């Protein structure tokens, strides 16, 4: 009955906050067809196929432009700088809402109530509606699970309606990218999904909403993982996709706060999420034992290859290289509990995967370099590996998360700088990507570098200035091969490094040009690379 307030009709069965045991039974029902079907692996975790979409679809993301959002959002068609916040008319929104609500009508529906945000004063109460059990399972893992008493007076602040099985046949007449859609309306406080079954759309959708509400309130909202040592020292790790946020924050010596989305308020750093979402391509249980051991009943594997005997081929990227496992955060043994939060960060680490092979494995940044690299948000990929030999493709994504920013990048920079300054925090740039060898730096060497950051080894090392980027790098560090610390050493001659460094420096300079129309931003050019 209460679902008719959202536009949904004739629902006979509501499955309200299903238990983990019920979701297991629902996923393994032998009568399911198509992409609803799950299969049981020998690790005890259920595995599913997410269908045509095996990752996010930024080209299909729209935000209703109305008097609530017109003058506050960072719009794709207005400011400087590329972003995916494409404006949507209220009229087209009503068309999309009718598509989704008719798809959900007459169905058996799963409804999951959950929180986004660890702190009662700023968290969003979210109600997710789906007709697919494993999608309800994804949101149960990834958001904060309310207690019985919190469900009693639950009042949603936001509604997410997942109409994955429907599509929009009028898209060409409406100026949209395709028949699929991921749409947000901040007047109605709703998210609609059509066409894509990929669960990450709901996770990153709610993160975009927190990126809108919080910085406005003086609270930093950060695309980062976070953890805390036995002495109470908090570290945060920013980074773009596949740079290592989950991998490197999940350390058995430190208590995990969270692996992907955090805020930073007057009391400290807090997780938005209740679970973890780890990349599993080529997963190695010797290199990632805590993540591998989280894969058991109530974890949800996505798009991995499951053999006839139920065993898992983690090396197989034939459906996608974005294979994934989600698990509630308590599948990790050493976490902060019962609430995922801690004090003020004193170490801020920017992870980048540099496929140009130019950046050092680690550098301590000056204050202005911190703002510069935060706004630049650089990473690069090997694009055409499949095409035999391949070259590198750069991404500049402001704040290491431009796909999720709802406000202008300088608004996130300003609140983050405020929090860092008050805590006496220091920032570091860590290349988890490539060097002159054409191979990624190993997880073992990356973990030893992080350890040397967190224990103050790096702070106390002798350093020199890497040219062009003007990055302070150490001459040596406990636990790390000394050779790799200077990226020039990993080439035959240092002139090979020089040529790539010049190519890369020019990409940074061109990218930063859009921030230099204010005085503060023009002054930051001096912190950036210099030809
Ligand atoms: N030196 C390294 N450090 C960290 N990760 C590495 C390294 N070398 C390879 N990897 C691989 O990179 C991937 C990082 O996955 P992870 O889930 O940590 O990404 P993430 O930054 O959390 O991004 P996403 O938001 O896409 O999940 C894993 O497949 C990991 O094994
Ligand atoms: Ca990510
Ligand atoms: Mg991850």
Image: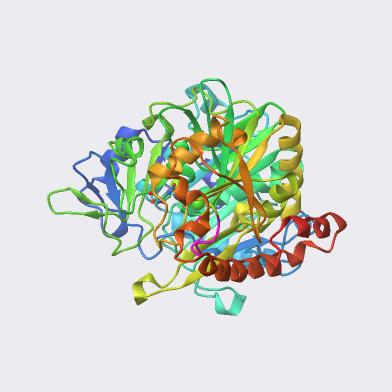
As displayed, is residue 494 above or below residue 462? below
Does the magenta stretch mainly form a helix, a strand or a loop? loop
Q: Which residues are magenta?
A: 353-359
Q: Residue furthest front?
A: 493
Of the pair 44 and 469, the residue shown nearer to us: 469
* 191 relative to 171, above or below: above
Is the C terminus in the top left, top right, bottom left or bottom right quadrant?
bottom right
Q: Nearer the viewer, residue 220 or 386?
A: 386
Q: What residue is rendered at 48% in x and 64% in y?
A: 381
Where residue 490 appears, x then y in whole percent? 45, 59
Model colouring? rainbow
Residue at the farthest right position: 519
**Whether residue 453 can be seen here:** yes
**Residue 22, position as x, y percentages in the image:** 31, 36
Residue 98, quarter of the rendered image:
bottom right
Q: Is residue 344 shown left or right of residue 54? A: right
**Residue 307: percent from the left, percent from the top?**
17, 54
The image quadrant of residue 40 is top left
Residue 123 coordinates in the image, percent (x, y): 62, 34
Q: Residue at x 68, y 66 (%)?
A: 511
Q: Residue furthest left?
A: 309
Count up the numbered dots: 0
User: Is residue 11 or residue 232 the one in the foreground?
Assistant: 232
Residue positioned most to the bottom: 173
- Please identify the quarter of the rendering in which residue 519 is found: bottom right
The answer to which of 105 and 496 lies nearer the viewer is: 496
Residue drawn at the location 27% of the way across and 52% of the way down: 314
Q: Is residue 354 magenta?
A: yes
Residue 111 in view, yes or no: no
Horizontal arrangement in the rendering, residue 505 relative to residue 438 (left or right): right
Does the segment drawn in magenta span residue 140? Answer: no
């Amino acid at each position: 009955e209460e679902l008719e307030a959202y536009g949904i009709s004739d629902v006979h069965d509501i499955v309200y906050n299903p238990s983990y045991d019920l979701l297991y039974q629902e996923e393994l029902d032998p009568s399911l067809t198509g992409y609803e079907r799950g299969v049981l692996t020998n690790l005890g975790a259920v595995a599913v196929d997410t269908g045509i979409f095996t990752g996010r679809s930024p080209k299909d993301k729209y935000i209703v432009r109305d008097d609530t959002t017109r003058d506050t959002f960072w719009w794709a068609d207005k400011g400087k700088g590329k972003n995916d916040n494409k404006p949507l008319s209220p009229e087209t929104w009503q068309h999309l809402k009718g598509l989704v609500t008719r798809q959900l009508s007459g169905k058996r529906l799963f409804v999951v109530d959950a929180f986004c945000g660890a702190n009662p004063d700023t968290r969003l109460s979210v109600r997710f509606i789906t007709e697919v059990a494993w999608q309800a399972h994804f949101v149960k893992n990834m958001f904060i699970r309310p207690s019985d008493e919190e469900l009693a007076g639950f009042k949603p602040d936001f509604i997410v309606m997942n109409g994955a099985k429907c599509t929009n046949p009028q898209w060409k007449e409406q100026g949209l990218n395709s028949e699929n859609f991921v749409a947000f309306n901040l007047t109605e406080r709703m998210q609609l999904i059509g066409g894509t079954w990929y669960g990450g759309e709901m996770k990153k959708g709610m993160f975009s909403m927190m990126n809108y509400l919080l910085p406005l309130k003086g609270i930093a909202s950060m695309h980062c993982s976070a953890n805390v040592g036995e002495k109470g020292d908090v570290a945060v790790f920013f980074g773009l996709s596949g740079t290592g946020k989950t991998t490197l924050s999940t350390d058995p010596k430190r208590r995990l706060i969270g692996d992907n989305e955090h805020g930073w308020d007057d009391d400290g750093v807090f997780n938005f999420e209740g679970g973890c979402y780890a990349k599993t391509i080529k997963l190695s249980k010797e290199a990632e034992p805590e993540i591998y051991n989280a894969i058991r009943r109530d974890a949800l594997l996505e798009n991995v290859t499951k053999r006839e005997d139920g065993t898992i081929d983690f090396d197989d990227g034939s459906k996608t290289e974005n294979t994934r496992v989600s698990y509630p955060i308590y599948h990790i043994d050493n976490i902060v509990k019962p609430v995922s939060k801690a004090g003020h960060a004193t170490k801020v680490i920017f992870l980048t995967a540099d496929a140009f092979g130019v950046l050092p494995p680690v550098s301590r940044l000056t204050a202005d370099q911190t703002q510069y690299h935060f706004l630049s948000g650089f990473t690069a990929k090997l694009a055409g590996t499949e095409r035999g030999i391949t070259e590198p493709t750069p991404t500049f994504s402001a704040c290491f998360g431009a796909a999720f920013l709802s406000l202008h990048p300088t608004q996130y920079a300003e609140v983050l700088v405020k929090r860092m300054q008050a805590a006496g925090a220091q920032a570091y740039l860590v290349n988890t990507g490539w060097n002159g060898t054409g191979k990624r730096i190993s997880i073992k060497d990356t973990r030893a570098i992080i350890d040397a950051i967190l224990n103050g080894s790096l702070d106390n090392a002798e350093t020199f200035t890497l040219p062009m980027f003007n990055l302070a790098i150490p001459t040596e560090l406990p636990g790390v091969d000394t050779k790799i610390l200077d990226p020039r050493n990993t080439y035959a001659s240092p002139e090979q490094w020089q040529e790539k460094a010049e190519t890369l420096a020019k990409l940074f300079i061109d990218n930063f040009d859009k921030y230099t129309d204010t005085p503060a931003g023009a002054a930051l050019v001096a912190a950036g690379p210099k030809l």
